[PDB]
Each structure stands twice: as C-alpha cells, then as structure tokens.
Length: 141
Length: 141
Image (cartoon, each protein chain N blue to C red):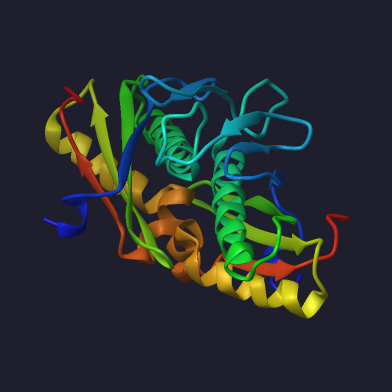
C-alpha cells in the first residue's frame, strides 16, 4: 500500500491460520495442512517444517534456473534444516541449507550455490536474520 | 560453529530434489506437490509455504499472548505473499494481518505488537525490508 512494490506483482497468494496450536493452516482455494506443536508427537506440520519446505523449494527452483542458463540438465537437490531454540518470549528459528549438484565438479557446485544464495527470494528474506547459513555438499548421506 | 545449534528444542529437515513440477517433503512426514506459481498446474509453491509458516507461527504466538492476558483464543492471522521482479532479480513481499475478534481494536493492536516481537518467523523477516504487519477487523480485500 505505502510500499508501492505491491502495486502489480507477478503473483500473489494468501495463507490463513485461525485455529488452536493443534489445528490447521490453509491457502484459501488451495492446500490445507494439519498443524500441531513441534513439542509433542501429534500428527501435523509446524512453522519450522513449512519454512524448510518453502526455502528448499525456492532454492531448488533457483538452482534449476541457474543450471538451465548454463545449458545443464537438472541434477541439483536442496536440504534445509530448521531448529527451534530459546525460551518463552525469547524463541528463535535457525536455518541451514545444504545444496548438492550431482552433475558437476565441486567448484561448479559451489559457484552455483553462491549464485542461488544471491537470487533465491526466500534466501534473500533471511539474509539479514543472523540465523541463516548455506553450504555446498556432495550428498545428504 | 554457531553454538545455538548445539542443543535445540526441536529440529526438522525438508528436502526438494525434483523439477519445478515436483514435490518437497519432510522425511517421515508431510510431502507436498509443488509447481510454478506462474501456471495453473496443481501444487503449492514457496510463496504459499512461507505464508503457511508465518501465519501458523503468528497464530501460535498470539494464542500465548491471549492466554497471558487471560483471554480466550479468538485470534486469526492472514499472510499475503507477493512475487515480484524479473530474471535474477526476484523477490517476495510478505504482509501479515492480525485480527482478535474478542477484543477492541486498541487491544488487538497491542497484541499484534507483542506477537510481531516474539514470533520466530517474524523475527527472521524483520531485517528483510519486505515484511509488514497490521491489525485488521476482517480479511476483506
């Protein structure tokens, strides 16, 4: 509104949560997920998981675009770990992404990781958080 | 070596190892179909997943704040996410809207301020320059 970057986006969506901790979150017209506290064993997802799903997907999409700009097939994969830390009124999330590119030498995988770190929208939102790290790996084993 | 990773409350991991028309998953947990937001194919996307994460986190934080004030849980949170930009210049914008049906607007605003400061996903986004939050009385428009 004040921020005129909202005036004509490429795409917009919305998400709602209007339930108790043991509840659901949903995209109106779209995906609904069961949610629950990460501190119990009940079925359901949580913000930590949902954030990891968001970032891993965004990084992977960005990596696919980079691969294509280099004339390469898609052989990349991303794993994101999210940690919940702290105490009442002092809670934080930590986020650590791992990027692999199976098709290529490690130096190329590292270069692509640097490229995607700079381009991925979710990565950019977390850049200044103090809580986000990213690395290149050869596998997730 | 960030020591905050040493003994967390909870950790999880998310993977995306597929094409844009693919899936993301939590090992042993939720798997979601994904797709580009720029087509009409089935599947979620990073924008949606981020909205689900933040709306859920804000709502959970709000539930704690309501309880601290001895009020029932009447809150609801909607998060809008926009995709803007161009090749190698893409960003997301995030706008949270918080309602607390059981209380007057000044109280709803006060609670919104409290959750903005406590919600882990909100804190991650604080320094992004792309995240705003407001108090509302409904989700019109």
